[PDB]
Length: 388
Image (cartoon, rainbow, N blue to C red; front, side, top):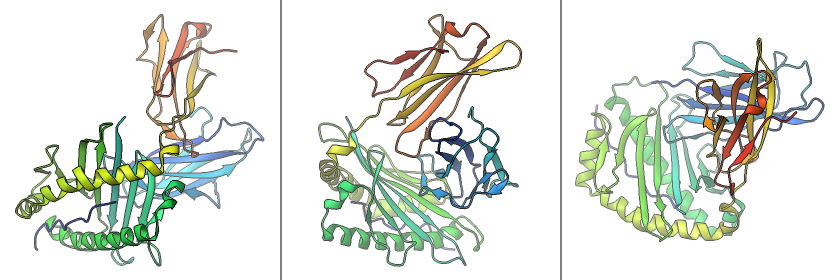
Protein backbone atom coordinates (compact mmCIF):
# COMPACT_ATOMS: atom_id res chain seq x y z
CA UNK A 1 0.00 0.00 0.00
CA UNK A 2 1.52 3.27 -1.18
CA UNK A 3 1.81 6.31 1.08
CA UNK A 4 -0.17 9.52 0.60
CA UNK A 5 2.32 12.06 -0.71
CA UNK A 6 2.54 15.62 0.59
CA UNK A 7 2.95 18.44 -1.92
CA UNK A 8 6.53 19.56 -2.47
CA UNK A 9 5.52 23.24 -2.35
CA UNK A 10 8.76 24.52 -3.86
CA UNK A 11 7.70 28.17 -3.68
CA UNK A 12 5.90 30.95 -5.51
CA UNK A 13 6.70 32.90 -8.67
CA UNK A 14 18.79 17.96 -19.33
CA UNK A 15 18.25 15.10 -21.78
CA UNK A 16 19.79 11.62 -21.82
CA UNK A 17 20.43 9.69 -25.03
CA UNK A 18 18.82 6.25 -25.40
CA UNK A 19 20.89 3.08 -25.68
CA UNK A 20 19.56 0.46 -28.09
CA UNK A 21 19.91 -3.31 -28.39
CA UNK A 22 18.32 -5.34 -31.19
CA UNK A 23 18.23 -9.09 -30.64
CA UNK A 24 15.99 -12.12 -30.98
CA UNK A 25 14.40 -13.80 -27.98
CA UNK A 26 15.74 -17.18 -29.13
CA UNK A 27 18.87 -18.05 -31.13
CA UNK A 28 17.91 -17.21 -34.72
CA UNK A 29 17.22 -20.11 -37.08
CA UNK A 30 16.16 -19.52 -40.67
CA UNK A 31 12.57 -20.66 -41.14
CA UNK A 32 11.82 -20.97 -37.42
CA UNK A 33 9.46 -18.30 -36.00
CA UNK A 34 11.03 -16.12 -33.31
CA UNK A 35 10.66 -12.73 -31.61
CA UNK A 36 12.70 -9.63 -32.46
CA UNK A 37 13.38 -7.33 -29.50
CA UNK A 38 14.26 -3.64 -29.40
CA UNK A 39 15.52 -2.77 -25.91
CA UNK A 40 15.83 0.98 -25.28
CA UNK A 41 17.36 2.27 -22.05
CA UNK A 42 18.91 5.28 -20.32
CA UNK A 43 16.74 7.93 -22.01
CA UNK A 44 15.01 11.04 -20.64
CA UNK A 45 12.46 12.68 -21.28
CA UNK A 46 10.21 9.59 -21.33
CA UNK A 47 8.45 10.45 -24.61
CA UNK A 48 10.01 8.17 -27.22
CA UNK A 49 9.05 6.97 -30.70
CA UNK A 50 10.15 3.45 -31.62
CA UNK A 51 9.76 1.76 -35.01
CA UNK A 52 10.90 -1.70 -36.09
CA UNK A 53 11.79 -1.98 -39.78
CA UNK A 54 12.19 -4.99 -42.06
CA UNK A 55 14.08 -4.33 -45.31
CA UNK A 56 13.62 -0.59 -44.75
CA UNK A 57 9.83 -0.55 -44.40
CA UNK A 58 7.90 -0.15 -41.16
CA UNK A 59 6.71 -3.33 -39.45
CA UNK A 60 2.97 -2.76 -38.80
CA UNK A 61 2.20 -4.45 -35.46
CA UNK A 62 4.89 -4.13 -32.79
CA UNK A 63 4.13 -4.55 -29.09
CA UNK A 64 5.59 -2.34 -26.38
CA UNK A 65 6.24 -3.01 -22.73
CA UNK A 66 4.87 -0.46 -20.31
CA UNK A 67 7.49 2.19 -19.59
CA UNK A 68 9.45 1.96 -16.34
CA UNK A 69 12.48 3.77 -14.97
CA UNK A 70 15.54 2.71 -12.99
CA UNK A 71 17.16 4.12 -9.86
CA UNK A 72 19.23 6.57 -11.91
CA UNK A 73 15.81 8.00 -13.00
CA UNK A 74 16.32 7.10 -16.69
CA UNK A 75 13.52 5.31 -18.55
CA UNK A 76 13.48 2.01 -20.42
CA UNK A 77 11.04 0.12 -22.61
CA UNK A 78 11.01 -3.14 -24.58
CA UNK A 79 9.57 -3.22 -28.09
CA UNK A 80 9.12 -6.62 -29.71
CA UNK A 81 7.60 -8.15 -32.84
CA UNK A 82 7.12 -11.62 -34.28
CA UNK A 83 9.37 -12.54 -37.18
CA UNK A 84 10.74 -15.54 -39.06
CA UNK A 85 14.40 -14.85 -39.88
CA UNK A 86 15.94 -15.66 -43.25
CA UNK A 87 19.49 -15.42 -44.57
CA UNK A 88 18.96 -12.17 -46.51
CA UNK A 89 16.10 -10.35 -44.74
CA UNK A 90 17.32 -7.22 -42.94
CA UNK A 91 15.76 -6.08 -39.66
CA UNK A 92 16.37 -2.88 -37.73
CA UNK A 93 14.95 -0.68 -34.98
CA UNK A 94 14.59 3.08 -35.37
CA UNK A 95 14.29 5.30 -32.29
CA UNK A 96 13.31 8.98 -32.38
CA UNK A 97 14.14 10.90 -29.20
CA UNK A 98 14.50 14.60 -28.43
CA UNK A 99 18.05 14.08 -27.14
CA UNK A 100 19.11 13.29 -30.73
CA UNK A 101 19.03 15.55 -33.78
CA UNK A 102 18.24 12.56 -36.02
CA UNK A 103 16.44 9.24 -35.47
CA UNK A 104 18.83 6.45 -34.49
CA UNK A 105 18.68 3.23 -36.53
CA UNK A 106 20.23 0.03 -35.14
CA UNK A 107 20.28 -3.04 -37.37
CA UNK A 108 19.87 -6.61 -36.18
CA UNK A 109 23.30 -8.26 -36.32
CA UNK A 110 23.02 -12.01 -35.60
CA UNK A 111 26.19 -11.57 -33.50
CA UNK A 112 24.57 -8.90 -31.28
CA UNK A 113 16.96 -13.03 2.33
CA UNK A 114 15.80 -9.41 2.20
CA UNK A 115 12.46 -8.51 0.63
CA UNK A 116 11.25 -5.14 -0.61
CA UNK A 117 8.01 -3.28 -1.31
CA UNK A 118 8.72 -0.24 -3.48
CA UNK A 119 6.56 2.12 -5.52
CA UNK A 120 7.76 3.89 -8.67
CA UNK A 121 5.72 7.03 -9.36
CA UNK A 122 5.76 9.14 -12.53
CA UNK A 123 3.91 12.37 -13.29
CA UNK A 124 4.51 13.80 -16.77
CA UNK A 125 2.92 17.05 -17.91
CA UNK A 126 1.83 17.44 -21.53
CA UNK A 127 0.51 21.01 -21.78
CA UNK A 128 -2.00 21.33 -24.60
CA UNK A 129 -2.07 17.56 -25.11
CA UNK A 130 -4.27 17.17 -22.01
CA UNK A 131 -3.86 16.64 -18.29
CA UNK A 132 -0.59 15.34 -16.81
CA UNK A 133 -0.19 11.58 -17.12
CA UNK A 134 0.12 10.00 -13.67
CA UNK A 135 1.33 6.47 -12.94
CA UNK A 136 1.91 4.40 -9.81
CA UNK A 137 3.72 1.06 -10.13
CA UNK A 138 4.29 -1.32 -7.22
CA UNK A 139 7.04 -3.93 -6.97
CA UNK A 140 7.40 -6.83 -4.55
CA UNK A 141 11.09 -7.73 -5.02
CA UNK A 142 11.56 -6.27 -8.51
CA UNK A 143 8.31 -8.03 -9.50
CA UNK A 144 5.51 -5.70 -10.55
CA UNK A 145 2.26 -6.61 -8.79
CA UNK A 146 -0.02 -3.52 -8.98
CA UNK A 147 -0.36 -0.57 -11.33
CA UNK A 148 -2.38 2.64 -11.65
CA UNK A 149 -2.44 4.60 -14.92
CA UNK A 150 -4.43 7.83 -15.05
CA UNK A 151 -4.54 7.51 -18.86
CA UNK A 152 -7.84 5.63 -18.91
CA UNK A 153 -11.53 6.50 -18.96
CA UNK A 154 -12.08 5.13 -15.43
CA UNK A 155 -8.56 4.65 -14.03
CA UNK A 156 -8.33 2.02 -11.30
CA UNK A 157 -5.67 0.08 -9.46
CA UNK A 158 -5.16 -3.20 -11.29
CA UNK A 159 -3.56 -6.49 -10.26
CA UNK A 160 -0.41 -7.18 -12.26
CA UNK A 161 0.23 -10.64 -10.78
CA UNK A 162 -2.31 -13.45 -10.57
CA UNK A 163 -1.61 -13.90 -6.84
CA UNK A 164 -2.84 -10.33 -6.19
CA UNK A 165 -6.34 -11.29 -7.39
CA UNK A 166 -7.18 -12.54 -3.88
CA UNK A 167 -7.56 -9.02 -2.46
CA UNK A 168 -11.21 -8.13 -1.98
CA UNK A 169 -13.07 -5.17 -3.46
CA UNK A 170 -12.23 -2.87 -0.53
CA UNK A 171 -8.50 -3.09 -1.28
CA UNK A 172 -8.82 -1.89 -4.87
CA UNK A 173 -11.38 0.80 -4.01
CA UNK A 174 -9.16 2.56 -1.47
CA UNK A 175 -5.94 2.06 -3.46
CA UNK A 176 -7.42 3.83 -6.49
CA UNK A 177 -8.84 6.64 -4.35
CA UNK A 178 -5.37 7.15 -2.85
CA UNK A 179 -3.87 7.21 -6.35
CA UNK A 180 -6.36 9.82 -7.55
CA UNK A 181 -5.58 11.88 -4.46
CA UNK A 182 -1.85 11.38 -5.00
CA UNK A 183 -2.32 12.38 -8.65
CA UNK A 184 -3.69 15.75 -7.53
CA UNK A 185 -0.60 16.53 -5.43
CA UNK A 186 1.72 15.97 -8.39
CA UNK A 187 -0.59 18.05 -10.60
CA UNK A 188 -0.12 21.03 -8.27
CA UNK A 189 3.61 20.41 -7.81
CA UNK A 190 4.21 20.31 -11.58
CA UNK A 191 2.63 23.76 -11.90
CA UNK A 192 4.66 25.46 -9.17
CA UNK A 193 7.93 23.70 -10.03
CA UNK A 194 7.91 25.69 -13.29
CA UNK A 195 8.64 29.05 -11.69
CA UNK A 196 10.85 27.51 -9.01
CA UNK A 197 13.16 26.43 -11.86
CA UNK A 198 12.54 29.52 -14.06
CA UNK A 199 11.19 27.33 -16.87
CA UNK A 200 8.93 28.35 -19.73
CA UNK A 201 5.28 27.36 -19.43
CA UNK A 202 4.78 25.29 -22.59
CA UNK A 203 7.19 22.38 -22.15
CA UNK A 204 6.86 18.85 -20.82
CA UNK A 205 8.32 18.00 -17.41
CA UNK A 206 8.43 14.95 -15.14
CA UNK A 207 8.29 14.17 -11.44
CA UNK A 208 9.62 10.79 -10.30
CA UNK A 209 9.36 9.21 -6.85
CA UNK A 210 10.75 5.98 -5.42
CA UNK A 211 9.04 5.09 -2.15
CA UNK A 212 9.20 1.89 -0.15
CA UNK A 213 10.96 -0.31 2.37
CA UNK A 214 13.50 -3.15 2.41
CA UNK A 215 12.94 -5.72 5.18
CA UNK A 216 15.44 -8.29 6.38
CA UNK A 217 14.69 -11.89 7.25
CA UNK A 218 14.12 -10.93 10.91
CA UNK A 219 11.24 -8.63 9.92
CA UNK A 220 13.25 -5.49 10.74
CA UNK A 221 13.56 -2.49 8.45
CA UNK A 222 16.85 -2.55 6.54
CA UNK A 223 16.36 0.58 4.40
CA UNK A 224 13.58 3.06 3.69
CA UNK A 225 13.25 4.87 0.36
CA UNK A 226 11.71 8.28 -0.29
CA UNK A 227 13.46 9.97 -3.22
CA UNK A 228 12.13 12.67 -5.55
CA UNK A 229 13.38 13.82 -8.94
CA UNK A 230 12.36 16.68 -11.22
CA UNK A 231 13.23 16.32 -14.92
CA UNK A 232 15.41 13.29 -14.25
CA UNK A 233 17.67 14.97 -11.66
CA UNK A 234 17.77 14.53 -7.90
CA UNK A 235 15.46 16.87 -5.98
CA UNK A 236 14.97 15.71 -2.36
CA UNK A 237 15.43 12.42 -0.54
CA UNK A 238 15.01 11.05 2.96
CA UNK A 239 18.31 10.05 4.54
CA UNK A 240 19.27 6.62 5.83
CA UNK A 241 18.64 7.82 9.39
CA UNK A 242 14.98 8.32 8.34
CA UNK A 243 15.09 11.64 10.21
CA UNK A 244 16.59 14.28 7.86
CA UNK A 245 16.48 15.19 4.17
CA UNK A 246 19.14 15.65 1.50
CA UNK A 247 18.09 18.42 -0.89
CA UNK A 248 19.90 18.29 -4.22
CA UNK A 249 19.75 21.97 -5.24
CA UNK A 250 18.52 25.39 -4.16
CA UNK A 251 14.88 24.90 -5.18
CA UNK A 252 14.53 21.81 -2.98
CA UNK A 253 15.60 23.77 0.11
CA UNK A 254 12.14 25.33 0.43
CA UNK A 255 10.61 21.84 0.40
CA UNK A 256 13.09 20.61 3.03
CA UNK A 257 12.43 23.52 5.39
CA UNK A 258 8.68 23.12 4.89
CA UNK A 259 8.82 19.38 5.60
CA UNK A 260 10.90 19.89 8.75
CA UNK A 261 8.30 22.22 10.27
CA UNK A 262 5.56 19.78 9.22
CA UNK A 263 7.29 16.75 10.75
CA UNK A 264 7.15 14.93 7.42
CA UNK A 265 10.24 12.82 8.14
CA UNK A 266 8.48 11.33 11.19
CA UNK A 267 5.31 10.64 9.19
CA UNK A 268 7.39 8.61 6.73
CA UNK A 269 9.38 6.78 9.41
CA UNK A 270 6.02 5.62 10.77
CA UNK A 271 4.94 4.53 7.29
CA UNK A 272 8.20 2.74 6.50
CA UNK A 273 8.91 1.05 9.84
CA UNK A 274 5.24 0.12 10.19
CA UNK A 275 2.67 0.27 7.39
CA UNK A 276 5.15 -0.58 4.63
CA UNK A 277 6.54 -3.53 6.61
CA UNK A 278 3.14 -5.05 7.40
CA UNK A 279 1.84 -4.76 3.83
CA UNK A 280 4.97 -6.40 2.40
CA UNK A 281 4.25 -9.27 4.78
CA UNK A 282 0.69 -9.57 3.47
CA UNK A 283 1.89 -9.41 -0.14
CA UNK A 284 4.67 -11.97 0.37
CA UNK A 285 2.21 -14.52 1.76
CA UNK A 286 -0.11 -14.29 -1.26
CA UNK A 287 2.80 -14.58 -3.70
CA UNK A 288 5.00 -17.08 -1.87
CA UNK A 289 4.57 -19.81 -4.50
CA UNK A 290 5.79 -17.55 -7.33
CA UNK A 291 8.02 -14.74 -6.03
CA UNK A 292 11.00 -16.77 -4.76
CA UNK A 293 11.74 -18.44 -8.11
CA UNK A 294 15.24 -18.59 -9.59
CA UNK A 295 16.08 -19.71 -13.12
CA UNK A 296 19.60 -20.99 -13.66
CA UNK A 297 21.39 -19.75 -16.80
CA UNK A 298 22.00 -22.19 -19.62
CA UNK A 299 25.28 -21.39 -21.36
CA UNK A 300 27.02 -22.10 -24.65
CA UNK A 301 29.88 -20.70 -26.74
CA UNK A 302 29.66 -19.61 -30.38
CA UNK A 303 32.53 -19.18 -32.82
CA UNK A 304 32.93 -16.26 -35.23
CA UNK A 305 35.56 -15.43 -37.83
CA UNK A 306 37.62 -12.23 -37.75
CA UNK A 307 40.18 -10.50 -40.02
CA UNK A 308 43.46 -12.41 -40.41
CA UNK A 309 44.21 -15.20 -37.86
CA UNK A 310 41.78 -14.20 -35.09
CA UNK A 311 38.35 -15.52 -34.08
CA UNK A 312 35.70 -14.41 -31.61
CA UNK A 313 34.51 -16.71 -28.83
CA UNK A 314 31.15 -15.46 -27.52
CA UNK A 315 29.91 -16.95 -24.25
CA UNK A 316 26.12 -16.85 -23.99
CA UNK A 317 23.94 -17.02 -20.89
CA UNK A 318 20.24 -17.54 -21.58
CA UNK A 319 16.98 -17.99 -19.72
CA UNK A 320 18.16 -16.87 -16.28
CA UNK A 321 16.34 -14.98 -13.52
CA UNK A 322 17.10 -12.73 -11.77
CA UNK A 323 19.10 -10.41 -14.02
CA UNK A 324 22.26 -10.22 -11.90
CA UNK A 325 24.99 -12.38 -13.44
CA UNK A 326 28.74 -12.41 -14.14
CA UNK A 327 30.58 -13.69 -17.22
CA UNK A 328 34.36 -14.09 -17.36
CA UNK A 329 36.81 -15.43 -19.93
CA UNK A 330 39.96 -17.16 -18.70
CA UNK A 331 43.30 -18.11 -20.24
CA UNK A 332 45.74 -20.16 -18.15
CA UNK A 333 43.65 -19.86 -14.99
CA UNK A 334 43.68 -16.04 -15.13
CA UNK A 335 40.80 -13.71 -16.00
CA UNK A 336 40.96 -11.71 -19.24
CA UNK A 337 40.24 -7.99 -19.47
CA UNK A 338 41.65 -6.16 -22.46
CA UNK A 339 40.22 -7.82 -25.59
CA UNK A 340 36.83 -8.71 -24.07
CA UNK A 341 33.48 -7.20 -25.07
CA UNK A 342 30.18 -7.28 -23.17
CA UNK A 343 26.54 -6.40 -23.61
CA UNK A 344 24.33 -5.02 -20.89
CA UNK A 345 21.98 -7.65 -19.50
CA UNK A 346 18.77 -7.57 -21.52
CA UNK A 347 15.28 -9.07 -21.16
CA UNK A 348 14.28 -11.90 -23.46
CA UNK A 349 10.61 -10.90 -23.17
CA UNK A 350 9.39 -14.02 -21.32
CA UNK A 351 10.56 -13.05 -17.82
CA UNK A 352 14.13 -14.35 -18.22
CA UNK A 353 17.26 -12.44 -19.20
CA UNK A 354 20.21 -12.85 -21.54
CA UNK A 355 23.84 -11.75 -21.60
CA UNK A 356 27.01 -12.57 -23.48
CA UNK A 357 30.72 -11.82 -23.17
CA UNK A 358 33.12 -12.25 -26.08
CA UNK A 359 36.89 -12.45 -26.47
CA UNK A 360 39.28 -12.34 -29.43
CA UNK A 361 41.69 -15.28 -29.49
CA UNK A 362 44.23 -16.58 -32.02
CA UNK A 363 42.94 -19.02 -34.61
CA UNK A 364 43.63 -22.58 -33.53
CA UNK A 365 43.98 -21.63 -29.84
CA UNK A 366 40.26 -21.83 -29.02
CA UNK A 367 40.69 -24.73 -26.57
CA UNK A 368 42.95 -22.55 -24.38
CA UNK A 369 40.03 -20.36 -23.25
CA UNK A 370 37.30 -21.08 -20.72
CA UNK A 371 34.17 -19.04 -20.01
CA UNK A 372 32.80 -18.83 -16.47
CA UNK A 373 29.17 -18.10 -15.56
CA UNK A 374 28.35 -16.97 -12.01
CA UNK A 375 24.67 -16.85 -11.05
CA UNK A 376 22.86 -17.17 -7.72
CA UNK A 377 20.76 -20.02 -9.12
CA UNK A 378 23.82 -22.09 -10.02
CA UNK A 379 25.00 -24.47 -7.27
CA UNK A 380 28.48 -24.17 -8.79
CA UNK A 381 29.66 -21.72 -11.48
CA UNK A 382 29.49 -23.05 -15.03
CA UNK A 383 32.72 -23.63 -16.93
CA UNK A 384 32.67 -24.34 -20.66
CA UNK A 385 34.68 -24.00 -23.86
CA UNK A 386 34.07 -23.72 -27.59
CA UNK A 387 33.06 -27.16 -28.89
CA UNK A 388 32.88 -27.81 -32.69
